[PDB]
Image (cartoon, coloured by chain):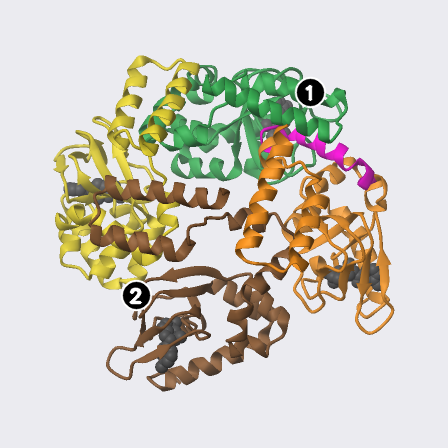
Chain colours: A yellow, B brown, C orange, D green
Amino acid sequence: DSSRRQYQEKYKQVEQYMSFHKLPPDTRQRIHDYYEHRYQGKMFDEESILGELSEPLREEIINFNCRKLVASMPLFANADPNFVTSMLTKLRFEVFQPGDYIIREGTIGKKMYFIQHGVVSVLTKGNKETKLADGSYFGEICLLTRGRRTASVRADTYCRLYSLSVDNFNEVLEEYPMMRRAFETVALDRLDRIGKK
Amino acid sequence: DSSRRQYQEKYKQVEQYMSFHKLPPDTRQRIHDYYEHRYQGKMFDEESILGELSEPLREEIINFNCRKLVASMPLFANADPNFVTSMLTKLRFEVFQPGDYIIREGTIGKKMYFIQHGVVSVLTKGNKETKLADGSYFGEICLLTRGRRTASVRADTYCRLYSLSVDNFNEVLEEYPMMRRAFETVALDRLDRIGKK
Amino acid sequence: DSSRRQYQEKYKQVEQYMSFHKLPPDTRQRIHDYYEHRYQGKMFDEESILGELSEPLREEIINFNCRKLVASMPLFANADPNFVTSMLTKLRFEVFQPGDYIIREGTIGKKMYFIQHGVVSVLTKGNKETKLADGSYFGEICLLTRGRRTASVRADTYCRLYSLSVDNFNEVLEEYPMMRRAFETVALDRLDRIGKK
Amino acid sequence: DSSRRQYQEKYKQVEQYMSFHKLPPDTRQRIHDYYEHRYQGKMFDEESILGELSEPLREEIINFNCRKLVASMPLFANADPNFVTSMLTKLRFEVFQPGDYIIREGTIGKKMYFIQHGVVSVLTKGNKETKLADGSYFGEICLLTRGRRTASVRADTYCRLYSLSVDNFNEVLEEYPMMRRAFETVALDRLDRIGKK
Ligand SMILES: Nc1ncnc2c1ncn2[C@@H]1O[C@@H]2COP(=O)(O)O[C@H]2[C@H]1O
Ligand SMILES: Nc1ncnc2c1ncn2[C@@H]1O[C@@H]2COP(=O)(O)O[C@H]2[C@H]1O
Ligand SMILES: Nc1ncnc2c1ncn2[C@@H]1O[C@@H]2COP(=O)(O)O[C@H]2[C@H]1O
Ligand SMILES: Nc1ncnc2c1ncn2[C@@H]1O[C@@H]2COP(=O)(O)O[C@H]2[C@H]1O
């Protein structure tokens, strides 16, 4: 009904823009596939729907929509449920296509990612590359150091991620200081397999 | 007419989102009841309507819509009417359901609440719990200390509240410094029945 | 056509809100009259229309819409036309009703006003009250001192004003420092007829 | 279809506003011509379309839409493609009419421009005026000095520009410090033909 019509109407607008700007069909297709994998044919207004609810109801809905992501992630599964809820509310859903570069080395990161579904390559230049999958996260090192990306991260497949900005990261750890160490440990651990400590 | 249609059309959108995300009927019902108690079947655009009026007209409307809340509250009833008007303009209407946690201990509060209608439990961990009702307020302690919630507050029933952010709190007291003491007194008084002073 | 329909449709929404909140007809009328005097039956989207034009075109339109206000005001008529244009772009149109209080003493002003059309009383408590009309401005003292309103200002009639915020005030004088003195002179002059210097 | 209808509907609104404010046909025409040259009869919602895509897809689209601008500009053609992409994302499309003043001397610039198509006169008061065309840029001096415009710049013809704000300028050079010198060189070089060094 109203959701499907909101999508096909918006996809329509997108299909016109591509034509006006005469984009390569090499590109229009990526755009088309992105739209499928991101919306599945139904477009809502989360900002509006969720903005119109009380905070307790948002937390109940968000905790449910992410119950599976939470169950796969050691960081959460054993944490205070209020820490978890406080992080889920600050995350933003992002989809990434096979080949896409989620993060670039040398760059100045301002956000991290939690993998809901998909596989990503951590090409840490030189050698000793790595793969992370569902339940893992990355991009935290810059949120702690405030330096530059230690590696690059490329979608091997369609990824569903949840990003968290440095602002929201520090705001959560301000409230739950205990949980910083959980991040530090995995960070310094990851830096050891490279150059950091 | 246009208000009712705006509601049932928006509630429609909400009912779809719930289905797409396959929420427990245990949850869909809470959402449904929330929507009833919050909108009563008519949805307006306060930001637009009120934004389109002069400041004097907003104050006249807001003072009238809150005349009853003002009459129940000792803080206001005896204060400079301009202090009162200046606070009413900064408040935000919030509804909370039976059982909901309005505030959590240990947490870093950034806003307080004034009860228009309803009853809330101040479970101050340990013992000596308390009940506040229509005309009372809470959550001011963190606005003064800038520390953490001294207790938890749970809706015993459907609550209608008006929240005030720390920013707007300090902005009002900047203009009406005399009124800080009224808040301090009730605060230090509340801290005594616990641990504060 | 589209403008008139946008107004009567929005006024419709306003008429419903008043009914829902059961406002005194003493108030609904003020609201109704305000809407007439502010929109004249046609509602546009300045933010959209003007936002869609180049800066030079905005300045040309704004200079024309305010040519009469500019001609009545000694501050402008003899100033660099670029100073003038730079001020006009930052102003915001405001209508005020007979009896309305535009400014209150003791209060912390963050904006000034230029009278396009109407008469206002500067009731400086005590005695020696004053009247300002088309082409005059007021509320500058707090923009300079950063203190409190030295008097109150009440609409004797329907006023059409243009307000300027302290931010935009200081931003203009940052570019045209010479013009501060023009404001200071009238300010210190106004303070002398009271208490300031 | 939907784009053309969005334009002619919005142009309609514009044509009414002009009439309501009784603008000189000397002005209505400039407005009309501006609208043609800026939209070409089709209006989209870039903020919405582009906001709904992943960052990698935006970069792919933006790099393509600006491939020609990039090919004409020595600054880019030889730079790290990621520096280039990082600048393109921050630019804003602006059209300017024959005679328009893009920049005024003595003024406090907060943005620079890259010429996609058109010719502009750098009237540096006094004497020794200059012309810049497709592929050139200007307005960088204030982004570096944080002072005032060294000259004025006037559209000799319809210009298509891309502006970059001081905020985005410093944010890019923060990530790609090497590229500051490329700007400094052309800047100090331009200052020499005048007064700067
Ligand atoms: N050896 C590794 N194993 C897994 N993830 C890594 C490794 N090295 C770096 N990363 C992740 O890659 C990210 C690149 O951006 P950050 O430096 O902010 O954070 C880095 C880590 O989260
Ligand atoms: N003994 C008490 N009686 C009533 N209210 C209380 C009592 N103790 C705490 N509160 C309220 O509970 C709030 C919890 O958050 P705050 O600490 O910011 O502010 C606290 C008070 O407003
Ligand atoms: N004697 C006066 N004559 C005219 N205007 C005045 C006089 N005294 C005060 N005002 C205006 O009234 C304003 C009240 O707010 P401000 O103090 O910011 O600025 C003040 C002046 O602009
Ligand atoms: N001699 C010149 N040749 C080309 N461009 C110039 C010259 N002098 C000034 N400009 C440009 O004109 C701009 C005016 O604003 P800015 O001072 O910020 O930056 C200046 C330069 O980019």
Name the element at disc 1.
Answer: helix
- How many callouts does the rendering have? 2
- Residue A61 in sight here: yes
Q: Quadrant of residue A18?
A: top left
The picture places residue A151, in percent across and down from the top left corner, at 23, 37
Looking at the rendered image, the disc whose residue lies closer to the viewer, 2 or 1, is 2
Q: State the CA–CA distance, disc 2 to disc 1.
A: 61 Å
Q: Which mark is residue B25?
A: none
Q: Residues within 10 Å of mark 1 (few under 14, many from 20)?
A: some
**Chain where mark 1 sits:** D
Magenta stretch: includes residue A95: no
| Image vertical order of residue C147 relative to residue D52, above or below | below
Q: Residue at x 41, y 60 (%)?
A: B94
Q: Residues within 10 Å of mark 2 (few under 14, many from 20)?
A: some
Q: Residue at x 45, y 28 (%)?
A: D46
The picture places residue D94, in percent across and down from the top left corner, at 56, 25
The picture places residue C173, in percent across and down from the top left corner, at 71, 47
Q: Is residue C63 left or right of residue A94?
A: right
Q: Is residue D104 left or right of residue B131?
A: right
Q: Which mark is residue B98?
A: 2
**Amino acid type of the residue tagged 1 in the rendering:** Arg
Magenta stretch: includes residue C64: yes
**Amino acid type of the residue tagged 2 in the rendering:** Pro
